[PDB]
Image (tube, rainbow, N blue to C red; front, side, top):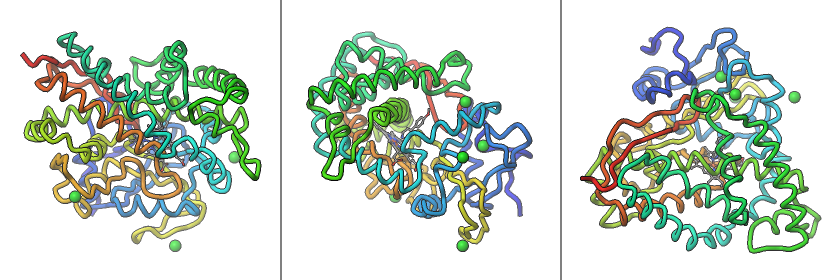
Length: 411
Ligand code: HEM
Ligand SMILES: COc1ccc(-c2ccncc2)cc1
Ligand SMILES: [Cl-]
Ligand SMILES: [Cl-]
Ligand SMILES: [Cl-]
Ligand SMILES: [Cl-]
Ligand SMILES: [Cl-]
């Protein structure tokens, strides 16, 4: 039988996510139609005009699609499954200039080069400065007494991690943070005036100036490694560095922010886990927070050929949308998925995507950011208590929290 969903329900409808996560609806698909055609009416496809997509709700199917990038393309339609309904096709395709929306072999070459920026050593070199910054963030928020946890706790450390990785001098971090904040959320009325196109252009201009400067004066950052030729002359051109910086400014910011906000929401809802976190400070917490938060609800692929997936014939040209928010609560993979368990180990969540060519290169930087900020929160505001309900972001594919009023002193 067909799944018990309202007629015309669209799992990428931003109007849903402005209010809630459609948890019951995803669970109904997993039970009754784990691969399900999500029809979309004319003009209501969020920028795609193909009649709908296949909703992918099971973790094993998300992994299969993610591993078979030879069939399931990121380039063909990009990986973001929802824009404003009137977005020009050319503005979707301009996103093919970042690694996330490339197929092999172009993706292979870029990822090999960019690897230089995300070596364990390079990320580990940011540990002590990010730890110092996390403690300062939490101390300053606790001193304010109460306020918006998103803005006073969750927001700054992911941005400082971007700045430290790129070696952005302190006097430039204000403008870098502004550009990065202008990239996300434009379907929400609170951000109706942001201009991601103009921000991206300014960022490219800034980043190409930086590439030209750092080739003269190599510095203790990843930039020197990215633009230095190897034995075979491989390196980012200045404009490719520009597109990488756009990608980093975009990717490195609000998904980690939202994991922090939603991790602390989870702790407010599960006091025994908060008590246990404060005592043991287990770094397994970061992965359970990312599973619980699933900051990217969904990314899509496009089939380059007919492909049979778990008994369903996907046709060439059709989109498949990987609902990480569903897969991360898959009863066949997780023991008690709706239990928040900061000791869950192993934790094979797909919050950073399915394993494969496009697996999040920032995963360990994200986990570090999360572990450092929650240690600082436990140190400086162990007794925080929510004051009022979170305000969610209107987005068809990002799970965002715009605002959350909290009493840091708990009294
Ligand atoms: C909790 C935070 C984060 C989440 C939930 C997350 C989520 C994801 C997901 C789901 C993908 C899969 C892309 C796909 O398969 O289509 C991805 C890829 C990517 N992430 Fe993240 N990410 C996070 C943090 C970061 C950070 C901090 C950075 C960099 C500073 C970053 C940079 C990237 C890049 C560049 C890719 C593309 C990799 C490629 O295409 O080869 N991400 N991320
Ligand atoms: C607003 O647009 C985007 C927002 C976030 C991402 C992202 C990709 C990979 N990892 C983390 C975040 C990409 C685009
Ligand atoms: Cl769509
Ligand atoms: Cl094309
Ligand atoms: Cl848009
Ligand atoms: Cl097949
Ligand atoms: Cl488990």
